[PDB]
Amino acid sequence: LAEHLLKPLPADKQIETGPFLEAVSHLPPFFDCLGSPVFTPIKADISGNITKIKAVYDTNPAKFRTLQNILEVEKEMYGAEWPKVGATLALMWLKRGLRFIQVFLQSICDGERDENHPNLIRVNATKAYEMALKKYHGWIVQKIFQAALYAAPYKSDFLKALSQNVTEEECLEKIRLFLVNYTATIDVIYEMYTQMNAELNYKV
């Protein structure tokens, strides 16, 4: 996780597309090590969106140099169907998966727990869900998330699975290091969606 740090934001806060895609491509693999087939479609959703944005970038790397460039080019290129089209739409859903991961990891690092059930991660995952995804899901997918939640590993096991023979405390400090530029980048992407009026609130 500290092997594939995101770059810091440059001074103009424009995120280069190519390095962003390379960086977040390291995230989906972690899903194969959570110990459950329940995670397979989740991995596919995030990976799928990365692939869709990459395929749009690959057509013209210079025109799509930055994430901002993607949104503004597609707005011009598509007309009325935008922002519900192309790499803009894929990144809109990608950012919510990335924010989910962010809120979950930060919650774990901040020592948030259920006193009653201390070695579970259900409260951390639930907070992350509420903050990033829930309002974009209809009732059925919410019900599926609730069920899926029970495939979650124990906290102790989750942390050991992300790690080297290293203490839990060491592993968390490494996660905190990863979260610095990760959080800043996602925040800038959310801000970009707001400024460009590209955010949509349809539920699935």
Image (cartoon, rainbow, N blue to C red):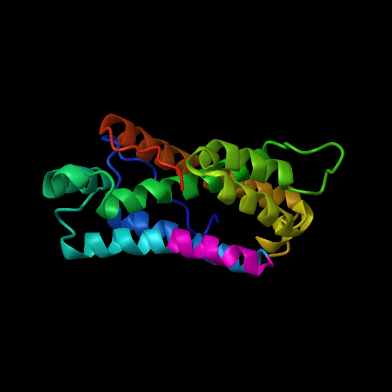
Is 204 colored magenta in this rendering? no
Residue drawn at x 14%, y 44% as measured from the top left = 79
121 up-or-down from 39: above or below? above
Query: 144 and 30: which one is in front?
Result: 144
Q: Position of residue 127 (x, y in %)?
A: 64, 38
83 up-or-down from 148: above or below? above
133 up-or-down from 56: above or below? above
Is 37 colored magenta in this rendering? yes
Query: 73 and 138: which one is in front?
Result: 138
Q: Position of residue 27 (x, y in %)?
A: 50, 59
35 up-or-down from 9: above or below? below
- Side of 150 relative to 49 (left or right): right
Q: Position of residue 130 (x, y in %)?
A: 59, 37
Quarter of the image where one finds residue 164:
bottom right
Residue 51 visible here: yes
Task: Name the main secondary structure of what is drawn in magenta.
Answer: helix
Query: 37 and 174: which one is in front?
Result: 37
Residue drawn at x 40%, y 37% as measured from the top left = 201
Quadrant of the image containing the N terminus: bottom right
- Side of 123 relative to 187 (left or right): right
Residue drawn at x 54%, y 55% as measured from the top left = 2
**What range is drawn magenta here?**
35-47
- Side of 194 relative to 4 (left or right): left
| Tag count | 0
Residue drawn at x 26%, y 43% as measured from the top left = 83
Residue 163 visible here: no
